[PDB]
Length: 95
Image (cartoon, rainbow, N blue to C red; front, side, top):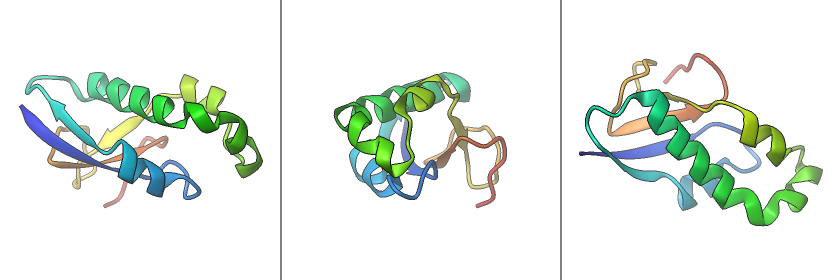
């Protein structure tokens, strides 16, 4: 297995909550990064479900977040599992 800690860069209004509440994962080695990204996406949506109505005034549409693909990057900017990864809605990331 690989223990992974995620730094979320999805929306500055909520990233600190995600970093505290749903940042730690254990991933079987050989899991593809896009499969792991679905696990992270599940945790983000599960974490934010109780506040979906409260997030709309903050500019966050949880329905849209539930449809988007989440992208995970190591500190080299690659789609490769690592002890520390970044989660973004964008297709590139700069550590």
